[PDB]
Amino acid sequence: STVQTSISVENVLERAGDSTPFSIALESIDAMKTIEEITIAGSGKASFSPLTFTTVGQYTYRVYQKPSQNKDYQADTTVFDVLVYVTYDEDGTLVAKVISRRAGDEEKSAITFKPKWLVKPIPPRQP
C-alpha cells in the first residue's frame, strides 16, 4: 500500500572542529523540482525528510551541494544520482530499494561531500 525511505547525506571537512555550514539539495528528476534542502554544520550526517511511494516504478532524484556561503571554502561539485525502485515482493507488499551513485562514473557510492579549504599554498611558478 505504502513504502517510505530516507536519503542520508554525509559532509566531511578537512579541519576537525570546523563547523562551517553547507547545504545539500534533493531534487526530483521526475517532477523537475527541488524537493528539500538540508544543512550540515562542519562534518556530520543528515537525512532528507522521508519520501512516500504508493505505486510501483523507478523514481529518479539528484543530490548536490549548494555553493559555499563561506568564501574561504569551495563546495564539493560532485553530483549524486539516487534511484528508488518501488516494487512488490512475494507477500504482496510495497518495497523500496534505494541506489545512490556518482552522476559521472556512475559507480555505486554513498552520498559524501568533501568541500575544499581554499587557504592553501599557491600553485607555484618556479624559477
Image (cartoon, rainbow, N blue to C red):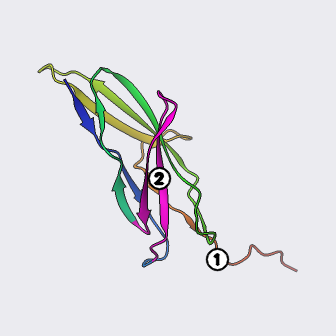
Q: Residue 108, located in which quarter of the rendered image?
A: top left
Identify the element where label 2 is drawn.
strand
The residue sitting at 73% across, 76% down in the picture is 122
| Residue 33 among magenta residues | yes
Between residue 43 and residue 110, name the one nearer to us: 43
Q: Residues within 10 Å of mark 2 (few under 14, many from 20)?
A: many
- Return the disc, 2 or 1, that comes first in the chain's sequence: 2
Q: Which label number is shown at residue 56?
A: none
Main secondary-structure element of the magenta-colored stretch = strand
Q: What residue do we see at 47% from left, 27% from top? A: 30
Residue shown at 47% from the left, 28% from the top: 31
**Is the residue under label 1 in contact with that under label 2 (CB below 8 Å)?**
no
Q: Nearer the viewer, mark 2 or mark 1?
A: 2
Residue stretch in magenta: 18-43
User: In which quadrant of the rendered image does the N terminus lie?
Assistant: top left
Which residue is label 1 attached to? 119
Q: Which residue occupies the foreground of this view, 104 or 29?
A: 29
On screen, residue 45 versus residue 31, left or right, reads left
Q: Nearer the viewer, residue 29 or 76?
A: 29
The amino acid marked with disc number 1 is: Val
